[PDB]
Length: 324
Length: 14
Image 1 (cartoon, rainbow over the protein chains, first blue to last red):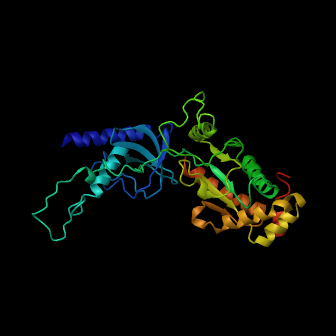
Image 2: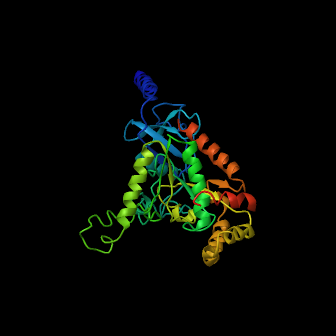
Image 3: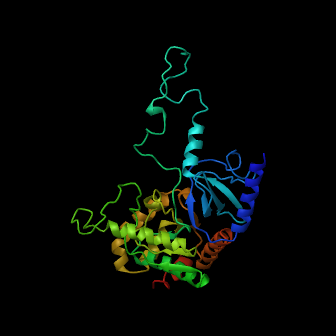
């Protein structure tokens, strides 16, 4: 057929011309799928071989069934990503190859209970939660430091301020760092259509500060849209589990002290003011250590400031080279 | 470890 070859050539030329266009946005998957094995891809053999929880950068538009995008991997080329509706269709295709999907079982009972698939056998039901396969995460993952104690106490503030200064100095002219005074742990997406749309309603949420949290959410989203690296200095993070189910999914950076004895003698080195809160500092430290390593993205366990600095610098250099 | 975790933590916010 000439039409399929013509559309193949048109898509290839469009990709070649749009390889050097500004990036539009980014998304993150949560399902295991490959973009090359599908027959509906407009270009065969040049699909995306992604897995669960991967990041894609989209630049231009194709149709309601596919988009054009690249991976955040180093050297990743341009491929086609199935659309939200297309992914829903392929997911329905995933749960149709089985013998049955609805209520009528096939346990040696054929010919009596036909039971045509009701609304319970389609995607119409199961809307109690309805977790979307695709989520619009920020284009650049925010960098956040956690540990080794509560934010707002001398040891943690200095052990994070030194790293913040190193990041600012090493990446000067290519990084923006801002302190997020407002709360961030409530970065929800599916609470309601608009909780507190107006501040003059004088409601429970209208008079609250939740709208500030959401506004900071779009502020972070638009700053990540700028493609420059972002580092957060919000003093309301003490465990990645508090910001793991949200849409941001920030790069969790852990600075850990090797032993509780070292941490508490460090705390003793400050004075009586921190001796007063030493108890809660130790409690938060042990709770955060009990968090498993796979929860975090990078670890900083070296006792030398420098070694940790070049460790973080190398990781962010890899990220920068990967997304360009 | 204490030597590296005492000077470095007391120079930033400090």
